[PDB]
Image (cartoon, rainbow, N blue to C red):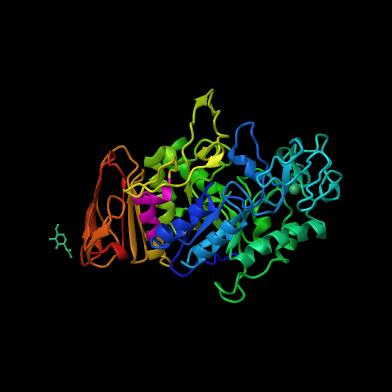
Amino acid sequence: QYSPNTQQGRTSIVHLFEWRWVDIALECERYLAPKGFGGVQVSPPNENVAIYNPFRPWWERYQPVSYKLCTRSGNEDEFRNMVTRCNNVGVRIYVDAVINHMCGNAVSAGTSSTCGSYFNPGSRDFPAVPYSGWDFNDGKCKTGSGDIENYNDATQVRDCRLTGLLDLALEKDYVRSKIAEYMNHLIDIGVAGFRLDASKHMWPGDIKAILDKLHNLNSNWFPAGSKPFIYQEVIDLGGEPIKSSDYFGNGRVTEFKYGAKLGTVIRKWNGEKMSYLKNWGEGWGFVPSDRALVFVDNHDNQRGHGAGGASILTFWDARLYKMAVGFMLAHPYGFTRVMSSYRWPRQFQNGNDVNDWVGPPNNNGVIKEVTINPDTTCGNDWVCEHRWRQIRNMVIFRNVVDGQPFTNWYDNGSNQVAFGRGNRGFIVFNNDDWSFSLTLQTGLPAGTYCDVISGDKINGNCTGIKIYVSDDGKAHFSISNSAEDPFIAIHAESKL
Ligand SMILES: *[C@@H]1O[C@H](CO)[C@@H](O)[C@H](O)[C@H]1NC(C)=O
Ligand SMILES: O=N[O-]
Ligand SMILES: [Ca+2]
């Protein structure tokens, strides 16, 4: 469950947050495949609560009503159509599995759901699954409110309602089977793995039991015996009884400390600086690289809805964001996930963003399609960070240097650092307030390379800056602290 099951040469997955199935299908064919992306993390494909207060917020998708693959992103067929089409072009589909709970216990009963299924949070009836009061942790939870109250009590964190969400009795074979039933359907459709949402709120043992029920990937597309990829959503920043290591027996875990400390460093907060990144990875209290699913930001914290808090960088900080991602995408630690967002009317008051609830672009609740601008950017308010040259090109960089060790590290003792990945790649950063002009050992083969950040290698030429590597691997670099993109990236496949 540790292997992403991407096909050799693909090393990242993009979170096409709130994208419809038809749009993702097209993206696999038109961009993801030819650009070498490994897979797509999709929003919960199961029926959820239709919330109108606020209007169609993005979080209404983490409030399940049934397991019908029928949401704002599309019905079951469109999902199949997507999974097939993406697989046929070597691009995987990872499902955001919301299996810890159903909806808010206070949500009105009725048919206010994405597929119309009737449900009753009050009487705990989700006849579409079906689930009854026998399937929830009401009796098991020992808190006075019934919800999670104190994170220092590892039991209540798992047995009580996460902010009011009805907690499924995951120790019951019946519930385990209804979830596995949901996940295997998806597996047999061709999905390559899952994001186990709210894993901290699930017992490592209960998750295990649910995985023992899981099939092996669809043998039409995957090697026989392919276990689905599993990355548990667990927010562990230390100082809490629950550790992410407790979930290593079930697969990978999101390393939330990653984007938190990376944003702290890049933002140069509390005295932190890039030169500290030399021992990036485990040396920072992060989980083992082979157990880490890393990312700069995620749909939650890019809104202040998650771990990392204030230091987290997002597309809103576009300049430092490309730099943050550039480093993540060049560093060998973990399996990388690129965020792909949409613009929302963000507006701060007294420090918080009051529009963080705003769902994806839409017309009367109907998610707007992703339009592709002539310059490959997206319209309809989709940010499409994965289409930004500096990101998309660093996505390719990771594939090209895949396997190569981390070496030839350089730092000025401040914020201009550089390192290489074997003899296949080299990247330089300058986050200081002054120009960086120095000849560095790149460990690369002599020749002329295209800087993939400022430009691209096209027709046997570079559209942007060019680096010249000498017979001794040496190469001169020059980045102005006021440069549009304060970092240069060259690799084997950008060589003229
Ligand atoms: C590279 O670009 C130059 C113009 O800057 C052009 O003369 C040359 O033919 C190009 N090389 C190839 C291989 O197309
Ligand atoms: O929540 N996924 O990192
Ligand atoms: Ca729970």
Q: Is residue 378 above or below residue 392?
A: above
Q: Is residue 286 above or below residue 303?
A: below
* Residue 443 visible (yes or no): no
Which quarter of the image is occupied by the N terminus?
A: bottom right
Task: State yes or no: residue 219 in magenta.
Answer: no
Q: Residue 150's spot in the image, x, y percent?
A: 74, 38
Q: Residue 116's spot in the image, x, y percent?
A: 70, 45
Q: Is residue 161 above or below residue 254?
A: above
Residue 338 versus residue 475: which sits nearer the camera? 338
> As drawn, which residue projects farthest toward the top?
350
Which quarter of the image is occupied by the C terminus?
A: bottom left
Task: State yes or no: residue 389 in magenta.
Answer: yes
Residue ID at (58%, 34%): 357
Q: Residue 427's spot in the image, x, y percent?
A: 33, 55
Q: Is residue 142 left or right of residue 91?
A: right
The tally of labels here is 0
Residue 403 versus residue 33: which sits nearer the camera? 33
| Secondary structure that dominates the magenta span | helix
Q: The magenta stretch spans which residues?
A: 384-396
* Residue 445 visible (yes or no): yes
> As drawn, which residue projects farthest toward the bottom?
224
Residue 173 versus residue 310: which sits nearer the camera? 173
Q: Residue 304's spot in the image, x, y percent?
A: 55, 36
Q: Is residue 334 above or below residue 64?
A: below
Residue ID at (48%, 44%): 341
